[PDB]
Length: 252
Length: 252
Image (cartoon, rainbow over all chains, first blue to last red; front, side, top):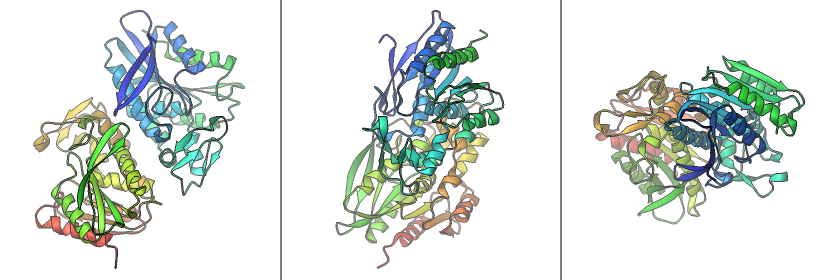
């Protein structure tokens, strides 16, 4: 609650949490959650904590339509999450305490991060992608998003989600926009260091997508964590966050 | 009949004018203006009038950051203009008076129209593009946007415009997203009828871009008005509007 911060994007309020090390000058990471998640998953909090222990500040926001941020979930698109990310980047870049800026994203957040870094390759210093969900485009082209199915050529106004996500409804604009989203093309513009982290037992996102990220980036590392799942649950959590912190540890 | 209307997009209010013919049921054209213009240029008003005389309703809205609508001009991008367009399309589609939906765009409005129709190819019935400003991507890659120059690899936060737009600043995000915008790839997905109208004397947008539209569209016509300029001025205004109305005529 001391950590609570808010910014505006187009008349929507985005709510986040800021973590800071002691001192007057520090690097900062923008940490981005995935589709249907929020800013306070175990993994994102572990990443924020490890970064803080290395003198790296962080902010983690709920994207529009998620958690405490404004907007209906059905009005969210990957594109306006990128716009959210840009508002956050304005906030961070304007801060007098902040030196270098990093992007960290998990699952769909990894797509937002990767594309935001492709739009700001001269500003973002380093990027970490954890199980980036670049599958979401092919999923949308197949008519199957998180087990919910629909006609990929007659996308209805809204598609109700299934399973653990019963009450919620994904927007048709999200699906139509995901079908044509230039994920790898825009991400490729980033030539600074990237670490990609994925689990060999990822059942949600085929790790061939993580591999393709590693292929197209001029300057990447790929970290296949043996037997890790998509969520990096259990001990995998600490592995992922550790790799993240190792990669972002500044040579101040 | 004319009336002022408003809709919400992401917490911003968009203001427009709705124009209706005799009767309670009609086709509806969404008319989109260009960069730094507004919903009431001479050409847009002439189009709305000719459509009404042809039994076709229309709405024309100020995009965010323009005219009477909310938002700062420097926070506008082509992407949130497409999002504005989607909100307008929602309003028209659910309107009980409406039969078929047409998009009509001028200059940058033509880019928004063409991309929106590519995302809603099963919903929009016809498209008219008037001097679509597909050049804006190449301009952004060259660092020269309507007389204002900048380093295309170190895009500043804002770029002050020059000339008759001397007071205003385009946002850096507008230029960064302009550089990677998949204009033709997305627009191509529209296979229903398109009419492209351009002046042979267009100094702002090279007519090869109109020709490229006509080439990628499966089902299009190209109308090169001899000696017309970019802002279809003087007599050319009434020709551009006529070609627009003729394409959208109900065909009794």
